[PDB]
Amino acid sequence: SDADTLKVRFTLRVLGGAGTPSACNDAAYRDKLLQTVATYVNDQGFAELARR
Amino acid sequence: LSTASVLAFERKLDPSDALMSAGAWAQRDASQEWPAVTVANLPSDADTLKVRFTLRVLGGAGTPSACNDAAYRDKLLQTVATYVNDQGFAELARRYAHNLANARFLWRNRVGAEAVEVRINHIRQGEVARAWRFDALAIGLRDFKADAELDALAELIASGLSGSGHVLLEVVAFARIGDGQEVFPSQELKTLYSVRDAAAIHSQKIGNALRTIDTWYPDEDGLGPIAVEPYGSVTSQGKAYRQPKQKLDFYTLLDNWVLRDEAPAVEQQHYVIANLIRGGVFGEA
Amino acid sequence: TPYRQVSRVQAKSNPERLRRRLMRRHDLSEEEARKRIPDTVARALDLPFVTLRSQSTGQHFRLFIRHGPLQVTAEEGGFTCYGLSKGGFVPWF
Amino acid sequence: SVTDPEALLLLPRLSIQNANAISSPLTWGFPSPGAFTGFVHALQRRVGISLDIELDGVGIVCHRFEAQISQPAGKRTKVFNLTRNPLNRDGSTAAIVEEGRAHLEVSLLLGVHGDGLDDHPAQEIARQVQEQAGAMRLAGGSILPWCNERFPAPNAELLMLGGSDEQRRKNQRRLTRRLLPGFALVSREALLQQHLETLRTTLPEATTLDALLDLCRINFEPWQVRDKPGWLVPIPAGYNALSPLYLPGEVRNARDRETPLRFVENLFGLGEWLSPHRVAALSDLLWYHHAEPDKGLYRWSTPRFV
RNA sequence: CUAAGAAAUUCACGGCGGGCUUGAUGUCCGCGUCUACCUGGUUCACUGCCGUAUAGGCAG
């Protein structure tokens, strides 16, 4: 009844190593997957996703 | 046959709390009215101190107040009987008379003094029966066991410890500490110790200078007397002496002489009897 | 003998149990006595010196190391300040 | 006492949110020890080769526990709190495939063996392990790094082969000051076997007899309760093959086409939570996993704990 | 390389009307607490000793 302010705190951790799967069968699919993730990253940053 | 479990002795040579009054010199024998330290500002008219306590020398040595085994009771009483058939209490009594002779019950109100005189009065009624005067700076305080007309004060305490008379001693100590410095009474839990608005010394502190006897100990006799204590220790200087590893110690010398009837040339038994005069809850288990 | 010896002579300048009224009394009034000097700027805490006590003292009143007066000359007659003069003879061994 | 550690490493207070609380088809509660023995091996293949050290043992010390459970009205059992999953592309609600979760505050006594102890300082190893271990997940739950009002708890390290016998009770009684608000989980395999020939009245197996140590079972007045050997729990104790081993490509739904496969079952055992003052040496408290791949036994225990 | 890897429970609400808890009562009767001690260990800043800057008459 005497408090007017809500305080909400949490901790975020941003890990990184984004396009690497934690599971994949084909070595060819992982090889042409992380290359496509790299030609996303090397052509334009995470800055458009990072701003949002 | 073995040691009992519950045993206590009572404090023989019990002093009273020594009240300390100041006062100007050349009023010494007419010291009916010298005021005491009125608290915490001390004058310069009064140039000497006045420390008075009474001392009772009771009697009985190895009779416990509360024993637990009767065979141990009679064995301890016959050990004290074989000690007292050998000699009186006069060797301990002259060493108590040595601490009476100076004012070593003035602990730090004596170091730094130009003339200290101690007057001991053996009183039967309010009338004084025999008086004494000693000069504290000029008599001993260490050793060599030699001053005339002090042997009568020794024989008095030997009679009173052996029980040959009621002994009541009324002592006065005049300390010329100087022309009204600030003396130091005892201190309670910081506040100076009082009695009725007069400063004084505790009777265990007055009494601690009286059983400061023990010049016999394992080390060489170059440092002098220690207070007769079981596991004989010093509480503030730090050195806790008479370790029970080596055998010269009160509980060892008591339990091997009562139960195991030891008698070589061991006639320094005065430490054990001086502990029994001190009294205390001795053991047990 | 070295150039080592310690001293204690002259340390009595500004008492700390009695501070606020030693500053300006010359039998006159105080109209401006709140923002005269900032005493809140300095903050120091060290006392490694000999505790030497007297009557009505706590642990120790104060002293600060004011070293620098040292000679190889001992005391002289008639010139005493507290108990010792400028310098003296004591070596290490 | 296989592969005695030359150095213990104390990851001091790891705070974990939403760890898996089911842990087996039969048990629930604190998660499986195989999760911890896989976590130390995931540390080992991220910093263990870059520092030429060997993280192989792990000590499990639970300080604080909390489960998302709820007791229903009129039942003495518990049910698990759940999450709302996303919908389907049809617009309908998906199935409720229930999962148990728990919050978790843990300490990890690691054990280090290699030659990288003698090249790096003891403080280089502990940071590179700790700040790595804040990037990983323990039991399906996020390891939450420190921020608070107090101070972050630091990652120590002993060298338990170094020192005299006074240091061998000065060091191993210094870490126990940092492990004492919680309890340590050790493996008790000799109790469940000696309780099996203790049952001479019936001739059971270990299944019904591990179920007869979880009980606060009440004995008839000749009421009374049968005696307590300690705080005993059922733990998953490894796996056991129910298939022969398959060549590393002949299943096309494996996690990878380079490792052999077996279909396995679980393998249940006994464990005890105990205060670390009962522990003589803290290296005896560590969890290893040994395998017998010629058999189908893939299990884990604390050896050298008498 | 972790029974691995993934996840939004959400919206709304009138618990409420009424009431005699009484009456009565014997807690008694006995008792030995004792002996000893150094706060001579760092236990609040009480009106009359010419200026932080290293500088200045303490019969306290």
Image (tube, coloured by chain):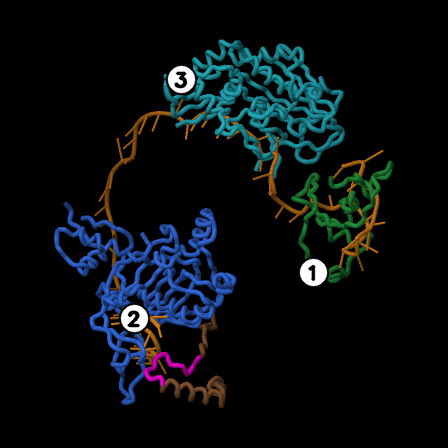
Chain colours: A brown, B cyan, C green, D blue, E orange
Q: Which element type, helix, strand or loop, lies under badge 3?
A: helix
**Residue to which mark 1 is pinned:** C40
User: Numbered disc 2: what chain?
Assistant: D
Q: Residue at x 41, y 85 (%)?
A: A34
Q: Amino acid at mark 3?
A: Arg
**Residue to which mark 2 is pinned:** D100
Describe residue B150's horizontal placement relative to residue B62 as left or right: right
Describe residue B78's horizontal placement relative to residue C32 as left or right: left
User: Numbered disc 3: what chain?
Assistant: B
Q: Which label sits on residue D169?
A: none
**Residue to which mark 3 is pinned:** B73
- Coordinates of residue B189 in the picture (x, y in percent): 57, 38
Whether D177 is drawn above or below B133: the answer is: below
Q: CA distance from mark 2 to mark 1?
A: 60 Å
Q: Residue at x 61, y 28 (%)?
A: B201
Q: Amino acid at mark 2?
A: Gly
Q: Residues within 10 Å of mark 2 (few under 14, many from 20)?
A: many
Q: Which element type, helix, strand or loop, lies under badge 2?
A: loop
Q: Which secondary structure type mostly characterizes the magenta part of the structure? A: loop
